[PDB]
Image 1 (spheres, rainbow over the protein chains, first blue to last red):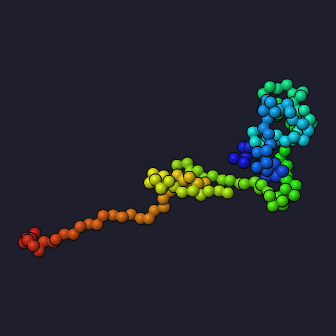
Image 2 (cartoon, rainbow over the protein chains, first blue to last red):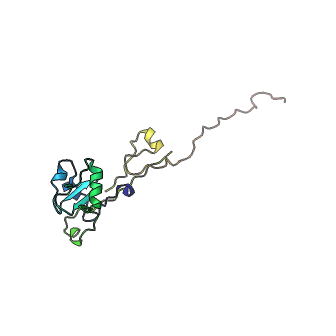
Image 3 (tube, one colour):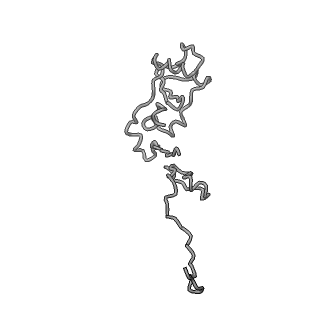
Length: 104
Length: 51
């Protein structure tokens, strides 16, 4: 559902872009640098300070990521697409899907 | 890019409204009821009555 996620698929985030973006894993959290995007729980983030998760001692990743946002190591990458993204005639434009189920 | 789908054509799905697509219809509308015809009497002229 849109309202549960907290992630934005239309913008500089995109959807097919979320393929080339590398999730947080215990191995990958070490290799992040300044400007590197990463998605966790399909919420893409952007790294403000290189080698984030250097001072963050939380082994649990969900909460470590959550205390990076407050320490401004990595921000949330919900961000609006610069206009040049949709004009290239190769454009991944976010899809909006619904489902209608009945409870009978 | 969203699919409307079809019922499986299984008479079980079509009556519940199950659909492979995005939408499950309320149900199978109604086209009306088909009763069975009331067969005819031969009346009673064939045999004397005398109520």
